[PDB]
């Protein structure tokens, strides 16, 4: 690619946002789409765009082939606005669930010597499986 | 991602590949030692039974969960679950379990749990026997139960893969009980080693496929990097040849 390839996109995607009443008062929401190769999220364009945008929804081929639809990998996805983009009841309903899902994935991967599981870890596993 | 890191990963994979064979040799030696010990224990137990018989002349279900929790463990656990469902009458039998999984399986079937222990107590065979043998004697003396048997969520190469289980009771008595428990433990250890051999054989293939994938990825990255570098160098060259190209085009277009 040329060296301009970052600016070419940035100056584009910066043309959206939420505006004040004296300058139109509207809001442009953008949902750009990007393709990765073999799950390599650390490509040039993919990363250039993760740096210009305010979040990412990562779709996983492993989840897609397993029958999950939509095949969204919540562990590899993020929203940087957080509860500021949600209403009060929705913010309270899902106040701390993404951290629980991350911890559940970590605990599922982690291997330990003890054959018994602490009760907090068991509760986290139950909640993560129910969330899935 | 340079060739140094790829070489380091390659040598690490080779080292683990050789260590797997070394561990296989060690595990085979351990298996042979345990086989000899079990045969000696069986001979001594037969002699002890003969001597005890000459001197003289509701069921208790003990459940143990597997050491770890993988796919094999889950399959064995569910087969043990159906075996419990098909070979226990809760209204007449008592079940003592060790381990969270078998304890949950007993709970879901509303069975009578004598007590709950920690799985690692099974590792110390001497203490395990000294405890549960006295418990079983106290039980059968009170006639609360008269049948005692042992089931493990583990596969046996003799039963075509089925679970290991043995009905110890009914058939100086405490020595025979300890000998039977020791024999059961030795059988379990022998089966575990026989499984471990095949597990190592699988790990070897996993390492080989990892090496193949890594080499493919490294070569794929290297070719692109080299091509881009060469293209940049020649573009830097060909910037300076524009004037001669334009002059030649103009001379050709002038005519003759």
Image: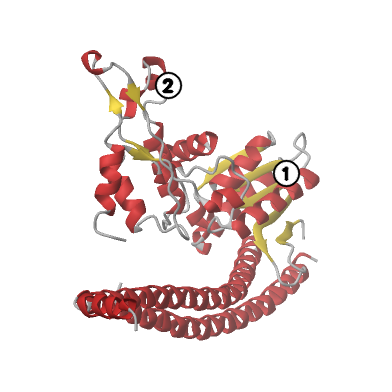
Q: Which residue is mark 1?
A: B145
Q: Which residue is mark 2?
A: A93
Q: Disc 1 sits on a residue from what chain?
A: B
Q: Secondary structure at mark 1?
A: loop
Q: Disc 2 sits on a residue from what chain?
A: A
Mark 2 surroundings: few (<14), some (14-19) or many (≥20) residues within 10 A: few
Which of these two is toward me, B166 or B41? B166
Which of these two is toward me, A6 or A88? A6
Q: Is residue B146 visible?
A: no
**CA gap, disc 2 and disc 1:** 52 Å
Identify the residue at image location x=52%, y=75%.
B209
From the top left corner, tell me how far across and down residue B1 is, in percent. Answer: 30, 72
Q: Is residue B39 left or right of residue B221?
A: right
From the top left corner, tell me how far across and down residue B177 is, in percent. Answer: 65, 62
Which of these two is toward me, B70 or A128? A128
Q: Is residue B191 above or below residue B169?
A: below
From the top left corner, tell me how far across and down residue B236 is, in percent. Answer: 21, 75
Mark 1 surroundings: few (<14), some (14-19) or many (≥20) residues within 10 A: some
Q: Is residue B205 above or below residue A126?
A: below
Which of these two is toward me, B8 or B149? B8
């Amino acid at each position: 690619y040329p060296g301009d390839i970052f600016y070419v996109h940035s100056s584009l995607l910066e043309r959206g946002g939420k505006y004040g009443p004296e300058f139109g008062g509207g809001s442009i929401t953008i949902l750009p789409i990007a393709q990765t190769l073999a799950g390599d999220i650390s490509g040039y364009i993919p990363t250039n765009l993760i740096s210009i945008t305010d979040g990412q929804i990562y779709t996983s081929a492993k989840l897609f082939n397993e029958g999950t639809r939509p095949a969204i990998d919540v562990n590899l996805s993020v929203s940087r606005l957080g509860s500021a983009a949600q209403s009060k009841f929705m913010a309270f309903a899902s106040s701390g669930l993404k951290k629980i899902y991350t911890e559940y994935k970590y605990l599922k991967r982690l291997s330990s010597f003890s054959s018994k599981i602490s009760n907090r870890d068991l509760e986290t596993l139950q909640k993560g499986k129910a969330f899935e | 991602m340079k060739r140094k890191d790829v070489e380091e990963k390659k040598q690490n994979l080779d080292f683990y590949h050789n260590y797997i064979d070394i561990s296989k040799i060690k595990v085979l030696q351990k298996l042979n030692e345990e086989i000899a010990s079990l045969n000696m224990l069986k001979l001594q137990k037969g002699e002890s039974h003969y001597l005890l018989n000459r001197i003289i002349n509701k069921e208790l279900y003990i459940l143990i969960d597997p050491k770890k929790l993988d796919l094999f463990s889950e399959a064995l656990l569910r087969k043990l679950s159906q075996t419990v469902k098909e070979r226990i009458r809760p209204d007449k039998d008592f079940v003592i379990t060790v381990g969270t999984n078998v304890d949950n399986i007993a709970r879901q079937l509303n069975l009578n749990i004598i007590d709950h222990y920690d799985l690692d107590l099974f590792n110390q065979i001497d203490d395990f026997a000294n405890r549960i043998g006295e418990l079983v004697d106290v039980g059968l003396n009170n006639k609360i139960f008269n049948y005692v048997s042992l089931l493990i969520a583990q596969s046996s190469t003799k039963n075509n893969g089925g679970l290991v289980q043995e009905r110890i009771v009914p058939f100086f008595v405490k020595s025979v009980f300890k000998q039977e428990l020791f024999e059961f433990k030795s059988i379990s250890v022998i089966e575990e080693l026989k499984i471990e051999l095949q597990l190592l054989d699988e790990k070897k293939k996993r390492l080989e496929e990892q090496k193949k994938e890594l080499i493919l990825k490294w070569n794929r990255a290297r070719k692109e990097e080299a091509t881009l570098q060469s293209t940049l160098l020649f573009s830097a060259f060909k910037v300076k040849n524009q004037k001669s190209t334009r002059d030649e085009i103009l001379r050709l277009s002038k005519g003759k």
